[PDB]
Length: 7
Length: 425
Ligand SMILES: [Zn+2]
Ligand SMILES: [Zn+2]
Image (cartoon, rainbow over all chains, first blue to last red; front, top):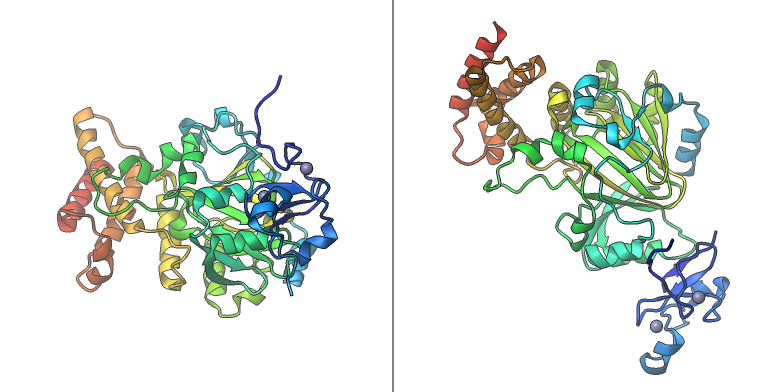
């Protein structure tokens, strides 16, 4: 699905 | 000292950029990789993700899936800093009088939105929100940066690419005009833009032709994306505001030699393999950071580099300060006969409406006993010459479709020439 990466 | 902001996940916490999150497909809510026990390395294998509350009734997660040189060449070349030419002006001091004094001949950078009159969403506004308001099913123009080709696709299909990992493609959305969507109510152009805009000032409310849909562009640029050198359609001046991230602008002044080089370069079929900045004398490197607004004058050849994921809002407009340049860039665009995806709709129709206003200004000048400014009179001569070329008996067929209703070009042209002749004395 849709994911939000890190930083 | 507090405020109200959106939250996500079961923990009901605001978005934290340092934590991995995955969106449940059922409830469309984002959940931390820690809260729901889904590690970041596990994310690619998940096709459909359902959060545990949704998994009870909507079914278990379908965890069964079953160029660089052009950027390097851009960063290799040394460019003068934009501080030399690009002026920094506070929004409160960027008025119509300031434009008249300086003539809007070089780009303006406004570090803070304060005073601009600009209306944009808060930085807690994400690409997921853009999909909801613009519309998940809306077809949008996506640019394959590596291949330098444009392809239409569903917005939900692109935003699926945006919210993924290991993006094998460099896709950008730089042509998304949302003035016809729910998001149109969230973005309003700066007050300086509305005052200068020809369509904002001189386009009738009863006009049967739709206004140029160039006012509320939205840009979603991925990390390490590239937009090649170009001139905005019709020499339209542009304003760019970076909501999130940052974007680097490479600005070239529309000198006579530079514009000729651009047209010869842009017309060449291999223009995607020729770095245009190496053909010009001075190309300025402007870094527009988060929350900053960049105003680009008419005819400037500019290219943008996006180092990080960036959300920006842009808009094109036409003003009386660069009538000559706007026509010249339109002539270059007309001769190129490039794709009409980035075009300026009804550019000639706006010119016809401007010419009608100039005739009324000439009539008012006789009544008010005051001389019109020389740049308007010169602009009237430029527009009048364009009117004759557009309505010439040999070339009327092309430009007739952009002729406003109940318009007599012969009467308008003859009246302008006489009034211009009077004002020259
Ligand atoms: Zn959480
Ligand atoms: Zn859910």
